[PDB]
Image (cartoon, coloured by chain):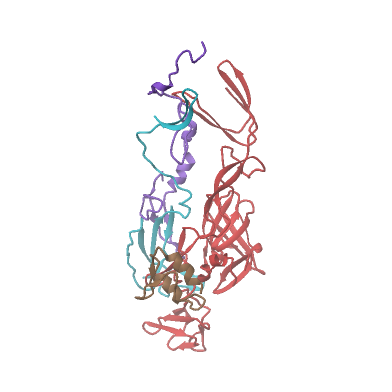
Chain colours: A purple, B brown, C cyan, D red
Amino acid sequence: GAFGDIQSRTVSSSDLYANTNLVLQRPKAGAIHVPYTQAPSGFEQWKKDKAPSLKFTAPFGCEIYTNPIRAENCAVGSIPLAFDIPDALFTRVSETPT
Amino acid sequence: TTMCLLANVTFPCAQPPICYDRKPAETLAMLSVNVDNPGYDELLEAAVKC
Amino acid sequence: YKTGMDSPAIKCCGSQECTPTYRPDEQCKVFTGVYPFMWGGAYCFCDTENTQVSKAYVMKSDDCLADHAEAYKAHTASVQAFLNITVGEHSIVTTVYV
Amino acid sequence: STEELFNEYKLTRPYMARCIRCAVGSCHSPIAIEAVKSDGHDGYVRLQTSSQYGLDSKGRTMRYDMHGTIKEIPLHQVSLYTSRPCHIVDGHGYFLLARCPAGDSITMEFKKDSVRHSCSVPYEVKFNPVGRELYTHPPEHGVEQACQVYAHDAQNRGAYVEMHLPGSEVDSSLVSLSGSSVTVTPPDGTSALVECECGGTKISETINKTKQFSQCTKKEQCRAYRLQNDKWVYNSDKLPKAAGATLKGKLHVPFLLADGKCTVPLAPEPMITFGFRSVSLKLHPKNPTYLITRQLADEPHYTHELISEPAVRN
């Protein structure tokens, strides 16, 4: 009845775990059918509830994307920098205005 | 490559010996034993057409 | 999910048995005292001692490929910026790793 | 290359199954319904029925089973409806694709000369909007979100259903009385088999012969089955099965759920009133519209609200 009542290891795993509360029932007198009673799709019930995405709820104003799972532009922290500058770039004084 | 079965004759799955417009139930029996096959779609679309 | 169901095995004045297949959540049960009907009349002539076997199992849906949800685990992230550096009017645009 | 697609449902036949709601009561129907799937967005469902489509007994046809003899009608005689009428788009094999509104039932019906056939099933059909604005009928103009609808062609993809031997479909139009005995008349090009209980235990397989039997007085004691070695059926629970390993192949399913593009509406522009460290929002939703706010700090304090009335949010 909840998220993950089907658990396939990958998309093409061909070996899935399933716990879906399936119970067979007695057929009606005079009819050829297979009557069962199981809990509904937990994936559908997860989709009905679905507290909103991390795209709308993330702190610091992040921008969650998909194909690599990544966040963008989270305005937090600070980047330190190291500059190993060679001595050739230091122009002398009198070659610049003053 | 993948070899399909009707007997102990491992024929190529793109080249079946029978087709449905010739035989009604022998093609269905050839498809019956070869369900567990990764080249079953090749055997399928070859086993229709002559 | 997609509850798959095998056709009911019916024997007239007999007794079936349960032969399992180890399909996911594969329930099986044998029902006695069954007088089934087809479209062309009744199926057995025996009143009692007939037997119908119900067999159900859970397989995943046909639209599993384009409609599925990936459960992951994440830890120890990696920050990576697209800087645009200019040092002494010499500009580069390089993906720096931080 | 449609003939390469249709060639696998040539191996199959339509059948009859038990429908719980028919035109009068509970019957055995040629248009019985196995499953309804409604998970595409803009109103497209995919019925798996007990009839076949796109084949003759031809372009737009339903092929069904009428007490053994396979019949056919054009597709524009078949209509189905959930709450409002649905619109049939195409068919391929045992599967039909319709554009349906939301409803708690499906009812398919066609009309022959003076016999009306119907099959109502208690299968819920839902309508799934795209985006953060919850419409009920897809709009006329807006923007285009990506979506997932059931594709309209019958292209072979990686999803299958499982086909099997049809079992012994019993009949009683075969068995008849003589003046003093019991007479079984199997049809031409078709072998029947007969089980009786008038002597001890009696059983026979007969072929192409009006074959009487002595010592049987009443034809209530003899059941005349019917046999078709060719012509697959679906693995239905409304059919009985054969004897021994049962399996003959698998077929692909048409109209799978593919990625697409869908047009979604665009809500009227909010009227924003600004103040010192505050923002007021006048909102006039045309149809119910999610407002989602969050702050750009370490505590976001996100607010999520379905708004369906003219409302002012500060």
Which quadrant would the N terminus of chain D be assigned to in this image? bottom right
Which quadrant would the C terminus of chain D be assigned to in this image? top right
Residue D61 position in % (x across, y down): 62, 66
| Res D232 visible | no
D73 vs B45, nearest the viewer: B45
D308 vs D147, nearest the viewer: D147
Q: Which residue lies furthest to the front in this view?
A: A94
Q: Which residue lies furthest to the top in this view?
A: A98
Q: Quadrant of residue B37?
A: bottom left
Q: In the picture shown, does residue A78 fall above or below D54?
A: above
Q: In the picture shown, does residue D154 fall above or below D267?
A: below
Residue D140 position in % (x across, y down): 67, 43
Q: In which quarter of the image is residue D88?
A: bottom right
Residue D180 position in % (x across, y down): 49, 89
D76 vs D144, nearest the viewer: D144
What's the residue at 49%, 58% (across, down)? D157
Residue D266 position in % (x across, y down): 63, 36
Q: In the picture shown, does residue A88 fall above or below C82?
A: above
| Res D169 visible | yes
